[PDB]
Length: 95
Length: 146
Ligand SMILES: O=C1Nc2c(ccc(Cl)c2Cl)/C1=N/O
Ligand SMILES: [Ca+2]
Ligand SMILES: [Ca+2]
Image 1 (tube, each protein chain N blue to C red):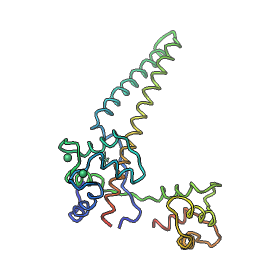
Image 2: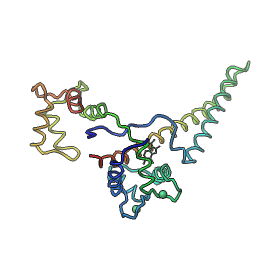
Image 3: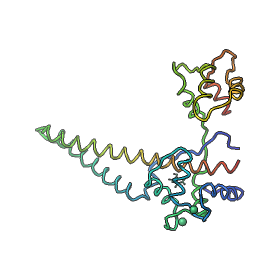
Image 4: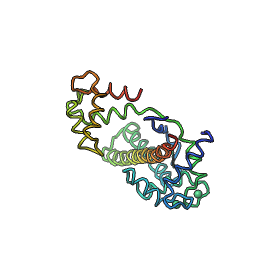
């Protein structure tokens, strides 16, 4: 039988977005990653006059959006393993 | 994502592990119960999200058709050798890839669900391949997963 094998974990974002709330979280945080990447680039590379306070504001907004994205990714990883736990328990009835 | 008919009858028996009342649907309440009996603590939102990933019709609960259907999307397995080796490393104090037989007996008879000293004997008979009172657990795990 299966011996010591367990369900293989999945690959990418291609699931669990049916929870529109994570979807709302992903789409807002990713727009903000785009937003603050642009504004940091502009305020450091497309100006003669680097306004450090402006860069600080957008660095704080940037780290916020990145870690929001990280946080959604870890909750997807957690949901998949919770699901793989049920699939693994079910699968012991094949023994 | 398409498997055998024998497994259909098998997954039906699995379904009763989940349908704690036998009403033909899995609710979040029963899924919380089952998940907690496996040593996990999912939030109410995590339970609603697992049901909603399966829930074909939208009635908030999983039936065997929806249960069987998501089983096929998750049929592939992978070997567990590296995960088992890291469980052994937890007890590798020196980080040298060894755990003494005495240390292994102490762990197996004091932590988790435990083993009898007789059960531990058989285990160490197999684990100490070189008979030197030290378990090279990567070797021992490769022997058990081969
Ligand atoms: O995205 C998934 N949702 C799932 C999976 C596997 C099993 C179960 Cl019960 C659910 Cl609700 C998934 N595998 O990717
Ligand atoms: Ca039920
Ligand atoms: Ca249903």
